[PDB]
Amino acid sequence: ADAATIAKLEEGFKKLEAATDCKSLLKKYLTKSVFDQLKGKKTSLGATLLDVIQSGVENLDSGVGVYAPDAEAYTLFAPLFDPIIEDYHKGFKQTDKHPNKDFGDVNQFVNVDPDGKFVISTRVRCGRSMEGYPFNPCLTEAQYKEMESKVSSTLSNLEGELKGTYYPLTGMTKDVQQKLIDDHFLFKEGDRFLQAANACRYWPTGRGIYHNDNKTFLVWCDEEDHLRIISMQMGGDLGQVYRRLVSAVNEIEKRVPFSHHDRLGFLTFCPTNLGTTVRASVHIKLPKLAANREKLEEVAGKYSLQVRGTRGEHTEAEGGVYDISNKRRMGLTEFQAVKEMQDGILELIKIEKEM
Image (cartoon, rainbow, N blue to C red; front, side):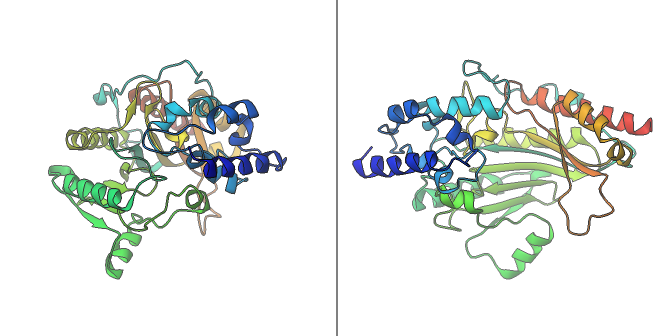
């Protein structure tokens, strides 16, 4: 690590002490003892501590404030990453190992609302970093093109349910944009937190969108992580959504190896998405539980569920509509995470019926 970067690191640290208002996990765990042991180190691909914390220094309001420049950095800079991970993922000690991938007995997953009267739509997401490339902080332009032609080639040779079409962002027509905007499939350049992390360079080179013909499978190449992989549909057939996801992820891995770490799970750009990288969610109507919020907050904790209200434009009538997702991503398998989610929704609907 060169003297010019070490100087810029010394600036950011004094800027963190000078921000007594900052509540970011970066400021919490970047002690002077850790900072002096990491500031001079660099990965074998060339990423410095500055490529980790720059975005958290430029954005003092940021919640986490660190990002991973390459896969190797989670090891080289573990003295800062490990305590941050402990904090965000409550109960993931610095010595615990995350289980290896296990999609489990996928047949055990069912429809959580067979009569469609409660769940509007069902969604399961995961992400992957492609093995052999650095993450978005350090991707060169040539690397962006190589990834695009590989993901495009891979996703285009998908057959059956996943038969689709890849739309690259570079030189996208105005017509496709609307058609993709219409289907909620498009993404744009990242917010202020990604821009400060160097995560939005050479835009839109290397960025693309893939969706199947049935519009129940959707992949984003290089929006934030290398790959974001979603299975979605209307209704509450969590099982069907989840089984379609495992089919796709296994099939992509045949041609595309993923960046895995036998203690942190699947490696991603942001430490909030380590472990399973799995976020199973439903849009569900629970009007009775909306009145008695204390019961909903209590049952949500029983199944480790995050309850967010729907972001919306004209939603004043829909206060009893929720986006319920699974909160846990580490220290448990993919199968365990989605099962826990399913068990939750089943009980939430059961309670709603008893009101």
